[PDB]
Amino acid sequence: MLEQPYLDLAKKVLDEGHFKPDRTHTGTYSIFGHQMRFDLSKGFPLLTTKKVPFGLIKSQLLWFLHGDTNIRFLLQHRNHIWDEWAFEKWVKSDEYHGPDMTDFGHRSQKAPEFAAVYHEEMAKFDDRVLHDDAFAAKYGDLGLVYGSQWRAWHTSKGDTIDQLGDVIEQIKTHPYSRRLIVSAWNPEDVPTMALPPCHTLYQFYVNDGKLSLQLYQRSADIFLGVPFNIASYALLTHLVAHECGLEVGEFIHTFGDAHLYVNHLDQIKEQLSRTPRPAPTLQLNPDKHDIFDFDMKDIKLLNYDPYPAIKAPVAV
Amino acid sequence: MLEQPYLDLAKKVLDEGHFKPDRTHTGTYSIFGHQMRFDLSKGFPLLTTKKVPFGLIKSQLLWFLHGDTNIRFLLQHRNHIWDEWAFEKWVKSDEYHGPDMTDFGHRSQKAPEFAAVYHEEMAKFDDRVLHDDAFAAKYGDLGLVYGSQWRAWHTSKGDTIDQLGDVIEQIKTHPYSRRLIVSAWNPEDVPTMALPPCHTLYQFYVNDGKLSLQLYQRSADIFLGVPFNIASYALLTHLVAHECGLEVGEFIHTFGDAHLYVNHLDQIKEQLSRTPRPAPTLQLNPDKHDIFDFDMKDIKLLNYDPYPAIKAPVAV
Ligand SMILES: O=c1ccn([C@H]2C[C@H](O)[C@@H](COP(=O)(O)O)O2)c(=O)[nH]1
Ligand SMILES: O=c1ccn([C@H]2C[C@H](O)[C@@H](COP(=O)(O)O)O2)c(=O)[nH]1
């Protein structure tokens, strides 16, 4: 069934995970090393067993794909997923006069006089990102994040490389190429950076007329991250294919540490008794062909008939 | 048994490979995506089923590990594995007066008046690498190759980063770190380069007191490459561990295209009936602890009791 590769990792991390210390203290149980394969000529791997808002995914992606590094695109479609990374530097900055805010994170997460200040503070900022074309430019422009490592990797002497646009075309003119990779691991930018990307490298492969994509993820949160990460790159494998005029093949997700923090066991547990349902189908717009100009309505999912969603404590 | 993960990929590529066109024309049968796991606390994965000269491996490695890019180190221990990359630029150069030599490769491989000229021409050059401290410096120094992408990744404005030395120490001071990666994929140097590395990325992981290493290989030659590539990174996982004072855990080898060219079927076929034998053990010198100062005799293998080797047509 489509998403069974997922439910097999959950099960499998539970069953032979091993307690590991971590970035917070919230242990995780993890495994090192793992591949799971999705025949995308079968349905869209959106998890049926937990409600997943496609909406946040495809726009997160179209922001990647336009070469973007700016919050504003996301807030313009109430996709809040990165705000924290951007509110962070506003708060810790010298225009920011206003409450102490020193790493909210979890200071919010179990303290309510302060998990309220932060809220509007944050919405204060969101508003200020949308509407102030100048503020947005130094506090919303986020710096290095996937849109910028895929489509404008900075060089040694000058310039900036559109790593992805180059790869799509070496898919268009050299399909049998073992050298088709897009990387986001920039070694000079890695010591001192926020989240050194989790989606480190991907690679395409063409065989007999169908595309495929592999993902190396060096770190992963089985419950919050991976259901979303799975549709992101299977959305991408689908977009890039329509562009190259190829059929769809398989999405492969290779993991380095894959992990379940511990205040989430109870939740995965519950999800694991839900009997998966048939998977959604994805129609991509029949006329637009450069994918970089894509927009929301050029992509609309069908039969996603999910279970209810499940709620869960998050990161720090 | 140790090397059975290997013999299962051979079998498995045969059985459901799919003919793919390629760099030469020599088809390959390949698969995209594959992980195989080796519990190194069990023995050294040198293939027992085909004789494998450890010698070339450990010195190839010590050249990587000293940050080297120079032929001479290799020729000094008759490790010829890279000569071709280096003879190439001598021949195609304007000191080189002497025969036409235009990509030997296969012009040697089925033409004997010329698979002789080349031979001494090449030995002419080898000699000239050893003994001419100046020639060696512009024709033996190879440019970008693993010793240089691991230990001196060039930066944007200036400098050069010892990516590996940094990672070993974040193993020494931050063991539970999902961010421990060494990459060799340099995106700016990749369009115009010889062999964009095949061993793209690796990642370490510590759990409960034992190290592990994963390899992403975007391309692979099941018969010639992978038996060697397997001992290289399991040698490395072993060296880096002795340095961090850790036990040994697992080596994971994740493949992108994994492939068998077609004038090699017959050979793997034969090897696949050989009944694997017990695996060798590896003792590393008990006193030296910085691994970067290691040398040949600080590493000596035990009980490698291999089958005979098997001969095979090579690359182009
Ligand atoms: O798309 C994503 C992004 C992040 N994570 C998780 C991985 C870890 O749970 C945490 C990152 O912490 P580090 O790996 O950077 O230490 O976020 C995911 O699983 N999927
Ligand atoms: O350590 C190595 C080095 C190379 N190869 C193989 C991979 C392909 O068979 C060929 C490289 O050609 P490209 O992948 O660069 O196209 O060499 C290996 O299997 N192992």
Image (cartoon, coloured by chain):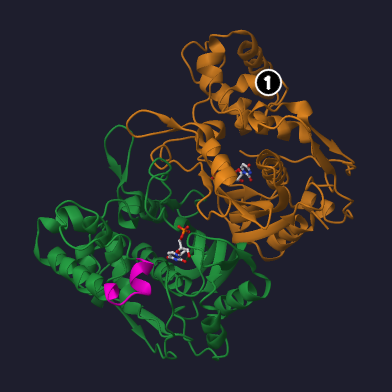
Chain colours: A green, B orange
Dividing the picture into quadrants, the one containing residue A88 is bottom left
The percent position of residue B247, horizontal first and vertical second, equals 73, 49
Q: Nearer the viewer, residue A20 or B65?
A: A20
The percent position of residue A195, horizontal first and vertical second, equals 40, 56
Q: Residue at x 17, y 52 (%)?
A: A138
The percent position of residue B159, horizontal first and vertical second, equals 39, 28
Where's ligand 2: which quadrant?
A: top right
Q: Nearer the viewer, residue A182 or A136?
A: A136
Left or right of B248, for residue A227: left
Dividing the picture into quadrants, the one containing residue B55 is top right
- Tag 1, which chain? B
The relative height of residue B240 versus residue A74 in the rendered view (above or below) is above
Q: Residue at x 17, y 65 (%)?
A: A125
What stretch of residues is rendered in magenta?
A105-115
The relative height of residue B293 versus residue B40 in the rendered view (above or below) is above
Q: Is A106 contained in the magenta span?
A: yes
Q: Quadrant of the N terminus of chain B?
A: bottom right
Q: Is B82 contained in the magenta span?
A: no
Left or right of A278, for residue B2: right
Q: Nearer the viewer, residue A261 or B137?
A: A261
The percent position of residue A305, horizontal first and vertical second, equals 41, 91
Q: How many marks?
A: 1
The relative height of residue B79 versus residue B31 in the rendered view (above or below) is above
Q: Nearer the viewer, residue A172 or A66?
A: A66
Q: Is residue A48 in view?
A: yes
- Which class describes the residues within 10 Å of circle 1: few (<14), some (14-19), or many (20+)? some
Which secondary structure, mark 1? helix
Q: Amino acid at mark 1?
A: Leu
User: Which residue is disc 1 drawn over?
Assistant: B75
Q: Residue at x 84, y 47 (%)?
A: B48
Q: Residue at x 66, y 30 (%)?
A: B62
